[PDB]
Image (cartoon, rainbow over all chains, first blue to last red; front, side, top):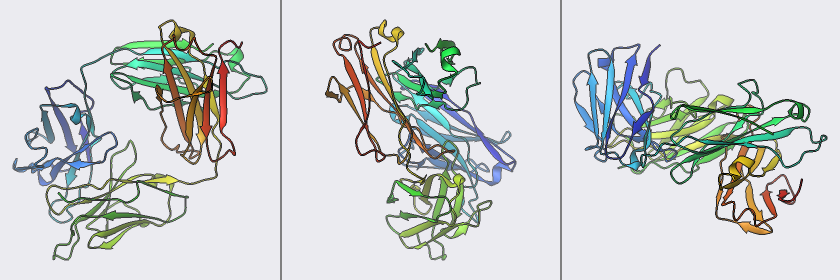
Length: 218
Length: 219
């Protein structure tokens, strides 16, 4: 039951700062180092710095020093990392890994990472548009429909097909950034028998704007 | 900085087969202590990386008997005996010798299987989207393998190269297929001027390109 739980989704704008967390459990927090890794959307993985929780002695990456400030909290078993003077080059996932310094030198466990998003300060509710074919023969059994969610910020979006009933055939695509907004689309393969005489309404949810939009496919 | 390099970004293998992932360092991770400071991790994929092998030839705890690290100097090699579904992911080789610590690019493990044809589909702009002044034509190419495919958007026989946004899903856990969603966007001013919009797809499972189309004045 040894685990590390990080803070979660971060709400930041350029120039500001943010404090990432990483609580450790199931073991003595002070007799194990704590590294901090950064990961761009798909560029790779890199070391930022570690911190001895027995004595706040820290060691940073010369390339992240002067922006990263690791500070522990022996009040219980927590760890933090501050990122100051944020630029869009900081929008990424940050992991916090334990370490068996002495014998193995092996980074045992890891946190779930924290997605830090630093944008041009936008925030917009999506526009959901129903996707239905232009024709369809009865012989053409499996009918495919869709839901186009365009013009939103920030991630993520909760896309469902009926209310959670339609599980199989659901293909919810990865949102690709437009100019200053996100856009995704999902589709479902339904038999040619149900659709014509049965409703299909995708449930779109945007927590960031707190809006729920149901759109029937016709 | 010590440059960590991993030759191939991706390497496909069928379940049961043996995989060999290579890693290459910039200097030499030897010590004299007799140990080579090399580390292998496994991001998988929306999950967190897990230590597989430490100090080059040491199977971490919990790690199965089938994984194996080997090499010397600058040539390092991870090896999976029997490839199982769980093993899918990006494998990372990282050094823990000099400062700062560097991580290799990342070699992904993809699953092989029989070739399947893309169930392409094309959808006209929604009535609601049009009233907003914009027009988007969506083309879905469902389940297919291999991953390679090419979508050429045609508007009245002319190839549209500016205004298209692709989106490929990750490899499905169940059927081991790949999905994609090609979306073209216009101004509902340029959309009304045209008749036909074609979504062409060049895949291995077709002697000729899969063509899906629709014409405006067509009910």
